[PDB]
Length: 122
Length: 107
Length: 167
Image (cartoon, rainbow over all chains, first blue to last red; front, side):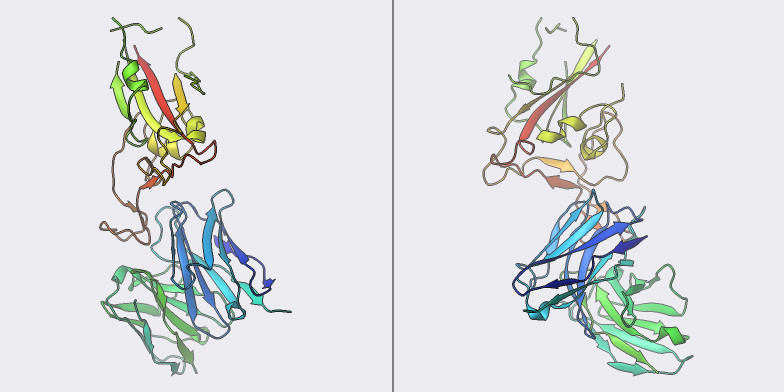
């Protein structure tokens, strides 16, 4: 069982990037996907989390306007899009979910490889 | 907002030495929702302890978690060569969910 | 005598899907009615039960025997052994959103045929008890149908009545 994130992304400032986190091996229905971002040699930052089944989304007030977390049960894939990209938004973004096979494991035990979004004018 | 303070900043110990890392919060967090994570250089984090005390599957026995209320501590009895990394403490109880600055384990 | 089939079909407000109301129906009984699909008895000339609920438009497919979806598995289940549905766009769709209708999104086990669940218990997914607080691994079992008259044809609300004859 694993979570496979999207490939590295190179975007211009002011555009929007969408990182795809695809779930495989565990019953994604009752799971919940959490998105965390980390810059090189810096502390982790938590964007938001989505209940996969209900679809209800809770966002940190920092990214309230800038991000939309979604999921698609047909592809077992969760998505996080960061809009109005700024240079400082360049970082690797992590996807975390709980192995909720039968019981939901009560902990974010599955973490994706991370996606490197690099924002620059050139 | 929940503030996660980790001490010390840089912790340097030799293999076979006990490592006592602590995570402190502003307002008490539900003990069931206090995890410890291990971050390797250039690697995705892997959860060590969930529920503040229950060890995760596939985690060595040396890692043990304790603490309740506003104080939580992770104890590594037998430090190993691969055990050198940074350790982050997250709470997933009360919104918003927060991460600690992380404590570094050095030689 | 005659049958009060006019008091379920032409009723003021139908109940939500999860709380599907059943009415027991001595009389012999001879709109657009988009889907008049009948499975239980061949369409030709002791009691019968009329089940009235409100489901999303496209969900009419889920109200069939041996069908697998959220509605059938969790909300209203039909045994393997007629159905009438009409669109109530102008009747049960408020512009600001008619969240009055609800459906069951989270359930531990699938619904037995003709079983009815009016539980409001928080779905305890994790191994930590949810104690009436919605959070991580603790999700409310019911979700609200966003019902606006400007919704697409599929998402428009469709009033449905199920007739289950019992000899």
